[PDB]
Amino acid sequence: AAADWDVYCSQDESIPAKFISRLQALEKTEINCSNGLVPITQEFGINMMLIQYTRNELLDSPGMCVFWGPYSVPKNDTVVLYTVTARLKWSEGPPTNLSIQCYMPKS
Amino acid sequence: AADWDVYCSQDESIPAKFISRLVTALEKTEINCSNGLVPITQEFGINMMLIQYTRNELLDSPGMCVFWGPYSVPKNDTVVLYTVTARLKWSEGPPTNLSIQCYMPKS
Amino acid sequence: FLNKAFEVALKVQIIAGFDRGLVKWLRVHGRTLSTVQKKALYFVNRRYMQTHWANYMLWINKKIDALGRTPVVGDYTRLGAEIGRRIDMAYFYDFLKDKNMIPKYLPYMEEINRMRPADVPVKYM
Amino acid sequence: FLNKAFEVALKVQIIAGFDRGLVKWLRVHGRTLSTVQKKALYFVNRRYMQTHWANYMLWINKKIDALGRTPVVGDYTRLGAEIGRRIDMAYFYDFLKDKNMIPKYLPYMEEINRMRPADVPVKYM
Ligand SMILES: *[C@@H]1O[C@H](CO)[C@@H](O)[C@H](O)[C@H]1NC(C)=O
Ligand SMILES: *[C@@H]1O[C@H](CO)[C@@H](O)[C@H](O)[C@H]1NC(C)=O
Ligand SMILES: *[C@@H]1O[C@H](CO)[C@@H](O)[C@H](O)[C@H]1NC(C)=O
Ligand SMILES: *[C@@H]1O[C@H](CO)[C@@H](O)[C@H](O)[C@H]1NC(C)=O
């Protein structure tokens, strides 16, 4: 339930990925991105966030999250992997850690 | 070093096996593990490395690499993800990055 | 944490910026959308601010500290306006419309849409 | 970056430990293996040392720095022996046999197998 985020990956690095979530109280949500740790607040109901494949710290919009990667995967040269992880800290219970993976066709 | 793979176990008590086969310049290989940055030298021909799913700093063997994780995966409640990444530095050219992933069935 | 006047300045400008962008997008894409779909997108704006508030606050505090002086509300107005114009909400407007994912308009959304932008609740981290 | 006597002590003990482990494993699993498969596993020992020499050196240096005195060759003998017995190579022996992945025995492997353990080349990083 808490792990179920709706992940929409792109086919081109120029178009950011979209993630949507819907919502043992949840105290904190932090996305571990290549450009840093990005806090987000999951409000009751629907939440939306963009994740970029590319980084330009000078021109990027405030608070942007950028994927880690690209990574090569074994035995498969047609795609590369982009990923982030997220940590959800709860009032009661151990934190949960989730992995968000997006495969991109290789140019 | 185009030829490499990871062979995952079905039990957290049994480490995964990473095998690479190098033909031929590769200056450096670093594995980014939950317990640290682990250097390895990929010699001409076959190279092997164990990757543990569990960490005990007191009892683990010297130089052991431990996966990051476990991570929950969205929309898939039957498995969890363990992963490390590898960075390969070449004499000339940009470094290459590998994603080493193992899915473990859940209890 | 943050003085209320400052918070209000931020929220008013952020939501005003997002809304200007939505008006712009709707002039092109709004013809086939229902009234409730449009209201749902205005809610999307306010909710985007809520979701990303803590994350905007990091950037804001960074910007404020670089002033080399005590801030005034005008500083927060300017930064709020900058967030309001820089966030590209059209990535979501297009995606939601293209996939027929514009959310069904529900009471909690109407409630947030009926508030003054100054009163939209945000959570600091 | 390491005195040759120290390096030699390490390599001799590491390979001796790995080899003892392989003998123990072969008593159980060796019956159906060909001579060249067994030679290949003896090569796997030496190669594992080569591959992991750099991370062994981190561990070694950490241990040496904590000795509470300057080291002598015996310290490297001891640490080498600890590495030699603690690395669980049987995980690879079992995997390679079970999956029919025991490597094809090639000249570079024989060359490494014919060397003195003291002479197996290692790369510092
Ligand atoms: C982000 O996660 C990586 C593992 O993928 C970890 O090495 C790093 O410490 C994390 N970053 C922060 C800022 O906690
Ligand atoms: C490589 O993996 C991707 C997604 O993980 C998949 O679409 C593709 O088919 C794989 N490679 C081949 C040759 O099929
Ligand atoms: C390991 O990689 C993670 C990303 O997965 C990164 O956050 C971290 O800085 C890296 N750690 C080291 C020691 O380089
Ligand atoms: C979950 O992931 C595993 C490994 O990636 C796969 O074998 C399995 O089919 C997946 N299940 C679902 C429901 O996606």
Image (tube, coloured by chain):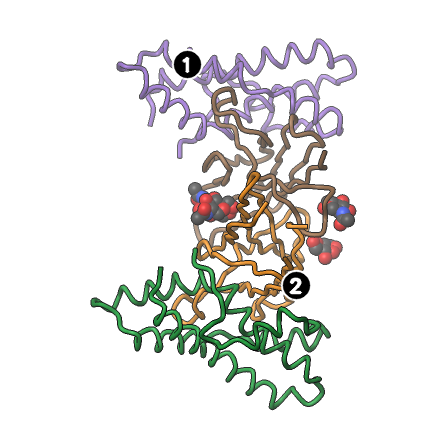
Chain colours: A orange, B brown, C green, D purple
Closer-to-camera residue (A35/C100): C100
Question: Which residue shows up at 65% across the image and 23% down it?
Answer: D91
Does the image show residue B46?
A: yes
Question: Which residue shows up at 66% across the image and 71% down it?
Answer: C107
- How many labels, in total? 2
Q: Amino acid under label 2?
A: Tyr
Identify the secondary structure beneath mark 2.
Answer: strand
| Mark 2 within 8 Å of ligand 2, using the beta carbon | no
Percent across and percent down for residue C17 are 47, 80
Identify the disc placed on residue C20. none
On what subunit does the disc labeled 2 rest?
A: A
Percent across and percent down for residue D64 are 34, 19
Percent across and percent down for residue A104 are 63, 61
Q: Amino acid under label 1?
A: Ala
Residue at the right extreme of this rendering = D32
The residue at which mark 1 appears reads as D9
Judge whether C1 appears above or below D36 on screen: below
Closer-to-camera residue (B80/D61): B80
Instruction: Locate the C terminus of chain D and report the quarter of the image it occupies.
Output: top left
Closer-to-camera residue (C86/D116): C86
Identify the disc placed on residue A8. 2
Cα distance between the residues tagged 2 and 1 = 56 Å
